[PDB]
Amino acid sequence: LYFQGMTTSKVTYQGDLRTSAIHLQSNNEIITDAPVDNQGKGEAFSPTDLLATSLASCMLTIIGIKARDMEIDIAGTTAEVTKVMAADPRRVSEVHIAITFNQELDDKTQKIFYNTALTCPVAKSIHPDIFQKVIIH
Amino acid sequence: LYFQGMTTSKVTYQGDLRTSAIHLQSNNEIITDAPVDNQGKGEAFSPTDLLATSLASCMLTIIGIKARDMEIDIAGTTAEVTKVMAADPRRVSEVHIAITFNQELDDKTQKIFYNTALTCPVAKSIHPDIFQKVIIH
Ligand SMILES: [Cl-]
Ligand SMILES: [Cl-]
Ligand SMILES: [Cl-]
Ligand SMILES: [Cl-]
Image (cartoon, rainbow over the protein chains, first blue to last red):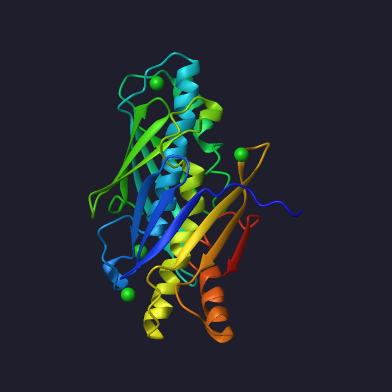
C-alpha cells in the first residue's frame, strides 16, 4: 500500500545522549537522557524509563475510562513504577506498578480495575516475556 | 526475593483521562492524554504515542553512543515517528521511524547506525510482532 499516515511525533537528537520529542497534534515536549552509567546527562527519563512509565500511564487512563463509566472519581490515584532490566541484550524484563487509589474500593471494583489495566493497549504492545506486576494499595 | 528496588517514576491520574509522570532522579515531568476519539483532552502524547516515541528516542540515543565512538557529530538528527494500531485488542502493530541525519553519511556508517538502532533496549522490549520500520534519509 502506497499511503503513509499522519506523523505521531518528531524526535530530535540534541547531543550528549539527549533527545527531544514534540507531539504534533498537542505541541507538547518530552526529553530523554541516557543514564550517567553510560555517559549521558541523566536529567530526564531514559528511553526505557519512558517505556515503563507509558505502561503505567496507559493503565491509569483505561482505569479512568472504567471509573468514569462507573461514576467513581479516582483523581489523585498514583502509580509507582519500578523497572527491572535483563542483559545480553539490554532490555526491560519486569515492570512493577504499585497503584494507590485516592478512596476506598470494594473487591469487585479493584478486580475490574486490575483486569482492565492488564488489557490496556501498552500492556499488549510490550514484549510478552516482560513480567507486568500490578499491585493495588 | 524480599528486596524491592529504586522507583523509576511516579504517575498521577489527574482526571479527564490525563496522567502526569515525574522521574525521581531527574525530577522532570511528562503528561499523557487520551485522544478526543475516546473523550480525552488530547493536549499531550497518548500512552501508546509515548511508547512509539520511546523506541525512536532509544534508537537515536544508541546511535549517539556509536557516533560518539566514531567521532561523528550527529546533533540535529531527527526521527519522524508514525504508529499503526491493530484492533481486538487495541495495541500497536507498527512503528515507522524515518531518520534524517544532519550530515552526509557513507554506506558502511548508515548500516552501522541502522543495525545498532534495531538492537536498542526499547527495540528488544516491545512486542516482537510489531513491525519496527526504520528508514534513513
Ligand atoms: Cl555529543
Ligand atoms: Cl539497570
Ligand atoms: Cl474525570
Ligand atoms: Cl488509530
